[PDB]
Image (tube, rainbow, N blue to C red; front, top):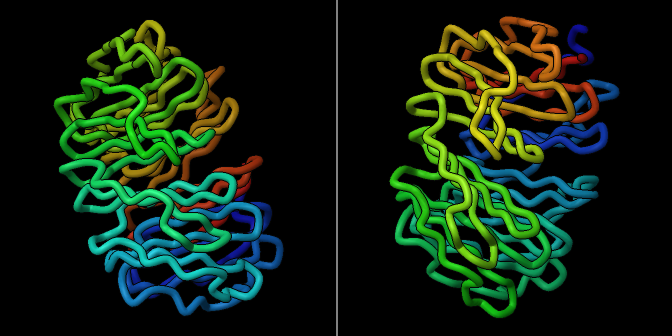
Length: 318
């Protein structure tokens, strides 16, 4: 249960992290994107990247979509780093990326949401979306669910361009959300969690949460993992709001979360990285992973990839 490989990382803070198969894609605040080999620890290449801070990364199959602070959205081949198609991108900072099938949905800090076709790069839908910075973006089955810094949550159907239903949203900035079937679940920075009906719009469940000022959220099935500034990492049920397991959490602000099967990984602002099993509540591992705030976590098949504010990228084994 140690590190699998040693990666050099970046010369500036890690701001985006993606992990697929045995390849890690990392973006830094200086615009640099690096492609790593998890099996050999060597970097595949230095991507020419963006001239601005990489803000989001999407890595699916062999195609990675990267957005930056200058509004560019690039689609390129993981094997060569070569641009596959040119997207016009947004005029404001890219703040959210979603990637499903051959469609890319990008959110911006001005509230705009654009829908691209990675086959032609043509702009499919370019709506104003929100009057606030888009903070969350989930896209599945030609349905886009977006959240914003003002607490608004919207549901669009790609192609039609209009909204399917209207949701009351939250009184606080959206931190994460998810959706499937009849249910849209969203979480705001004030700890509230709201479960919506994708066709009715009714607030089916409205919980105030068990923390004040949550920083990270994660949804897997009907279970929420919430990290807060006071260091508390909590696991509770979407249906009733009852807590499902007691974890001690960190003594520093939670800045990153990861959730896969029965294992929750949390990063804190002091660099510590703890790993629990959600069933037994037992701390599988705790480590001072980085000397700086953990800013991104990726977890696939008992492998934890972590990014930090000093630019270090590390690969852990469960």
